[PDB]
Image (cartoon, coloured by chain):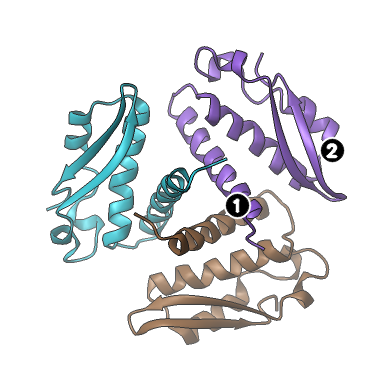
Chain colours: A purple, B brown, C cyan
Amino acid sequence: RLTPHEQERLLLSYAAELARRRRARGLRLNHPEAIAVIADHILEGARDGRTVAELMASGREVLGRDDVMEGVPEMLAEVQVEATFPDGTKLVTVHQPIA
Amino acid sequence: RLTPHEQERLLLSYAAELARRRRARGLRLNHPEAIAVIADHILEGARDGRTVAELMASGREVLGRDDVMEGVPEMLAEVQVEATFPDGTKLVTVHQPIA
Amino acid sequence: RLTPHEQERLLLSYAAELARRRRARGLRLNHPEAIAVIADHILEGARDGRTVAELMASGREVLGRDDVMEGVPEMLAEVQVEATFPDGTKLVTVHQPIA
């Protein structure tokens, strides 16, 4: 159902699409944009059947220092997201996804 | 300004976009994803100027068994969408859409 | 994580993506779709660090009479959106965006 959690997931997903569009036209992403993009990589990766361990590593390869504004890699200590896997929902933590 | 319901409709439209994105990615759709895609087909066909009769038909040719997870086509007895027509808002029902 | 207002702004941004999709398939936009597109132009221009005056001018050149249904240009007296620039939030109004 469209629980507040489901709405929130779809919002984060569209926010990631929008942040990707911004980056693709040359902008460096700000902190919430970078979070959306990394979170969306996790969400979609889980939907593909990637494992938590795979996502913990690949979520660190999505954005680099060049992709985000000054200060963003330092402010983004980790991204934590509940993703849906084949074997249920799991919290995925990507540590230090940019630096 | 968007009403909380308008926001609901747009969220479900985006969910269908994400579903079509996943299907494009080679993923067989689950139950809610399939619903979102068929729902969206109806809403977009109504916007195009299609009749309720046309949409009940075309709605059954959006996704086949190959496009969805095993079990989904039997879970999806119907998809109902309130769609706006020049004639008014009507509930459009697509029966056994995966078939 | 998102306020009502943030949710609404993200959904209005999505509405423009949907309006672009409708246009791409050969639809002329209606009044609310046109509002979304012009609003998106402003919001994205603001994010880009364009100036209010730049956007008030370029907002008049996003959609032409061909892009919208007959009688829509006359319906669109103005499109007003709050947008956050590098120097903060401003109400931006695009006047007579089509004709």
Which residue is pictured at 76% across the width and 30% down the height?
A: A93
Q: Are marks 2 and 1 on the same chain?
A: no
Which residue is pictured at 53% across the width and 30% down the height?
A: A33
Q: Which residue is mark 2?
A: A51
Residue B76 seen anywhere in this rendered image of the structure = yes
Which residue is pictured at 56% across the width and 70% down the height?
A: B39
Residue in the foreground of this view, choosing between C61 and A57: A57
Which type of secondary structure does the marked residue at label 1 adopt? helix
Going by the image, does B82 lie left or right of C92?
right
Residue B42, how many percent across, how many down? 51, 73
How many other residues sit within 10 Å of disc 1, few (<14), some (14-19) or many (≥20)? many
Residue A24, how many percent across, how many down? 48, 30
Residue in the foreground of this view, choosing between B3 and A98: B3
Residue C60 seen anywhere in this rendered image of the structure = no
Residue type marked 2: Thr
Corner quadrant of residue A72? top right
Residue type marked 1: Leu
Which type of secondary structure does the marked residue at label 2 adopt? loop
| The furthest residue to the front | C3
Residue C97, how many percent across, how many down? 17, 48
Quarter of the figure with the N terminus of chain A: bottom right
Q: Which residue is mark 1?
A: B18
